[PDB]
Image (spheres, helix red, strand yellow):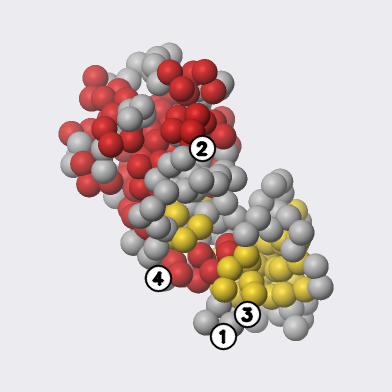
Amino acid sequence: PLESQYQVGPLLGSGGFGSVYSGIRVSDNLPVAIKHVEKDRISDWGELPNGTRVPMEVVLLKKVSSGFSGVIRLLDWFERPDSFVLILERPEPVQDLFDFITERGALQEELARSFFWQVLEAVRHCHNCGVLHRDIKDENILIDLNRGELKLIDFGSGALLKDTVYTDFDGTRVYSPPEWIRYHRYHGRSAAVWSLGILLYDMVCGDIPFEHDEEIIRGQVFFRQRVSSECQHLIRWCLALRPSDRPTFEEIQNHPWMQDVLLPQETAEIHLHS
Ligand SMILES: Nc1ncc(/C=C/C(=O)O)cn1
């Protein structure tokens, strides 16, 4: 029935992933994010148990909709003549890593260590559920200013996790791995490590390292900011040209720089002064 259930608010954001609004659950007054998607702009649809032709983004979300707050949760969805309305939980207050970074420029390695770690745990959850985000970046990461927790959002570019090879891609280009930029071929797991490599750099440097294909294809990494001798390692390791030479989510978390990580609360209580 909608409407009588949710009280739509202002336009949070939009873009190629759709349009999101700041609505409230009339039921218990729970802050939620309403997302809209045109059936014409849907890259690839999915399938539900009860045999219902619904968007893939919905299929992916439901597969990761758990108590784990590492990823955005899908409260409920609806179908319309030429579009779908996804109801997602909405943190309050909250700010995406993109604006956060633009606001406070580069981030202290300590703070990064915390975020990046939470991200890994999140991504691991997705893969652990046969789900590949395929579009990991600062814009798709929210920050629960209070609990200092992070969440992954927008799965419109993701797809079912498979050990084979992906020939298609609809995520952000600057974050895409070199193997794709050239041969338009890549493997989820290995590719994910590359995007994370870019992200990690984006945090410690305040911006992405590569801007053009030529830069990506090459793979040479330069640090404009002061980064620990070890952090640079982990970063370059992920950004390894040859996928096979890239670190695994395990090796990444076992990396020296990924030690003595702060807790969600401590982090917010120190860097988010709450
Ligand atoms: N505040 C907030 N909360 C949730 C979202 C979800 C976006 C998305 O699922 O694409 C976006 N913004």
Q: How crowded is mark 1: few (under 14 residues within 10 Å), some or many (20 or more)?
A: few
Looking at the image, is mark 4 or mark 2 earlier in the sequence? 4
Q: Where is residue 106 in the image (x, y as percent from the top left)?
A: 45, 26
> For the view shown, which residue lies furthest in the right direction?
81
Residue that carries the numbered disc 4 in the rendered image: 67
Secondary structure at badge 2 equals loop
Q: Where is residue 21 in the image (x, y as percent from the top left)?
A: 71, 59
Task: Report whether 260 appears left or right of 237.
Answer: left
Residue that carries the numbered disc 2 in the rendered image: 184
Disc 3 Cβ-to-ligand 1 distance below 8 Å: no
Residue at mark 1 to residue at mark 3: CA–CA distance: 6 Å
Circles 4 and 1, Cβ within 8 Å, touching? The answer is: no
Residue at mark 2 to residue at mark 3: CA–CA distance: 31 Å
Which quadrant of the structure image shows residue 238? top left
Q: What residue type is labelled 3?
A: Thr
Secondary structure at badge 1 equals loop
Q: In which quarter of the image is the N terminus?
A: bottom right
For residue 197, above or below residue 219 = below
Q: How crowded is mark 4: few (under 14 residues within 10 Å), some or many (20 or more)?
A: few
- Disc number placed over residue 52 in the picture, else none: 3
Which quadrant of the structure image shows residue 177? top left
| Foreground label between 4 and 1 | 1
Looking at the image, is mark 2 or mark 1 earlier in the sequence? 1
Q: How crowded is mark 2: few (under 14 residues within 10 Å), some or many (20 or more)?
A: some
| Foreground label between 4 and 2 | 2
